[PDB]
């Protein structure tokens, strides 16, 4: 449908110049749609970015809530999440730039809307950590919120450094190393 | 000072209005100087953003080098880095909005310029790790670049989460627990 066609073009255009500079007109042209056609599916520019996050990151999130259920341990569940995330971004240069660089917006309402979608991802982390503690796999006394900030911050900084390096090295190849740093930390 | 008066007014205006709505005229008004005096020191709005980051980072790094030579172990140095990072930002509401939100420009030419200023701090993290590696304090097989990304992303996301909650809780008090999470990870035992 034209809805997804438009989201896919928006990823391209938004990645090119940045969300702020991106123009709805450029998005239509790139989608090979008329200008008014865009307004047939989206209210405005912000609705395009929010929906892009909903469709790209939101789908990923839903998929992970399902797929982590088959992994026995907290470590395996986190391994799946990091590996699948790096894989989703490694498959699309534009999507890597957008989902990393447009994640935290200055405008309050736009930020809240994007944060709402990303809460889903944080809920997955908290759940993995909560259950891991009850099974005895995860550190007893662990502050779940803080440990989720370290896991999400680590994943995010790893992907953003790769984006700032033109995505030139194999991100997916790092998933296990990133996992072991989170599981065992830096001490010997 | 004229240069620092402008940088300080820029922090305020950019925090309060968002970088895109922070034009030179607004900064000039905020600093109490004329537009032409802004340009006597800066090229444009972008130059003010980049220079505010370079100036604030530079002070931060000189203090860091000063304090961490006292410390013996890699864990002691990281403890100082975390607590000093959290303290600086808890100490200046508008600067934290600038660092966590306004400096995160997605245009790539500009973002590269900003990111080159981060290199000095990342370099400090890499030296703590490599010193630790030589002294046998750091886990065998640990990759320095990845460990640096973990340390800085964990620190930075802890600050972003606190900014997202309107800086309403005591960030600084979380320093030690953030350190222990980086040092031993989430595994039980
Ligand atoms: C004011 C108060 C202050 C308070 C503290 C500061 C507040 C923060 C300010 C806000 C700004 C942000 O948004 S910071 C939060 C988000 N983070 C970022 O945007 C940082 C993204 N990272 C980067 O842009 C970069 O890492 C730099 C520019 C910072 C430094 O780049 P660098 O010096 O070249 O070093 P590096 O990135 O390691 O790249 C070197 C080589 O290694 C490769 N490489 C890099 N990482 C890896 C890796 N994990 N595994 C394999 N290879 C890797 C690269 O491809 C390149 O290869 P080859 O080319 O040779 O093949």
Image (cartoon, coloured by chain):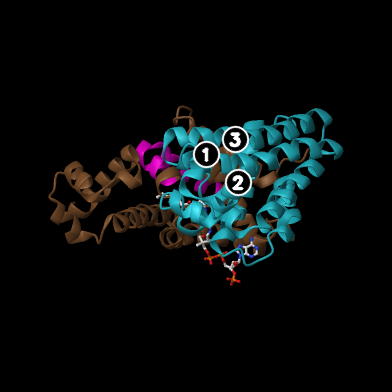
Chain colours: A cyan, B brown
Q: Position of residue B111 (x, y in %)?
A: 44, 58
Question: Left of A69 or right of it: where is A103?
Answer: left
Identify the mark nearer the N-term, 3 or 1: 1
Pinpoint the chain carrying mark 1.
A
Pinpoint the chain carrying mark 2.
A
Question: Left of B174 or right of it: where is A139?
Answer: right
Q: Which residue is mark 3?
A: A117
Question: Please, is residue A17 above or below residue A37 in the view?
Answer: below
Q: Which residue is mark 2?
A: A2
Q: Residue at x 77, y 31 (%)?
A: A133
Magenta-colored segment: predominant secondary structure: helix
Q: Position of residue B51 (x, y in %)?
A: 32, 57
Question: Please, is residue B123 above or below residue A52 in the view?
Answer: below
Bounds of the magenta segment: B74-99
Q: Which residue is mark 1?
A: A40
**Between A104 and A46, the one nearer to me in the picture:** A46
Tell whether position A154 is magenta. Answer: no
Tell me if mark 1 has few (under 14), some (14-19) or many (20+) residues whose alpha carbon lies within 10 angstroms of its own: few
């Amino acid at each position: 449908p034209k809805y997804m066609q438009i989201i896919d073009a928006a990823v391209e255009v938004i990645a090119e110049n940045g969300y702020h500079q991106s123009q709805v007109s450029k998005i239509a042209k790139q989608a090979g749609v008329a200008d008014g056609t865009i307004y047939l599916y989206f209210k405005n520019k912000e609705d395009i970015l929010i929906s892009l996050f909903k469709e790209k990151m939101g789908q990923f999130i839903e998929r992970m809530e399902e797929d982590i259920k088959e992994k026995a341990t907290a470590k395996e569940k986190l391994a799946l999440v990091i590996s699948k995330h790096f894989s989703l971004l490694a498959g699309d240069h534009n999507l890597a730039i957008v989902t990393q660089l447009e994640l935290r917006q200055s405008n309050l309402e736009l930020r809240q809307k994007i944060n709402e979608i990303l809460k889903g991802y944080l809920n997955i982390l908290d759940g993995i950590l909560t259950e891991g503690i009850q099974s005895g796999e995860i550190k007893e006394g662990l502050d779940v919120r803080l440990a989720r900030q370290m896991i999400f911050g680590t994943i995010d900084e790893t992907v953003t450094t790769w984006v700032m390096n033109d995505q030139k090295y194999d991100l997916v190849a790092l998933s296990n190393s990133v996992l072991e740093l989170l599981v065992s930390g830096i001490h010997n």
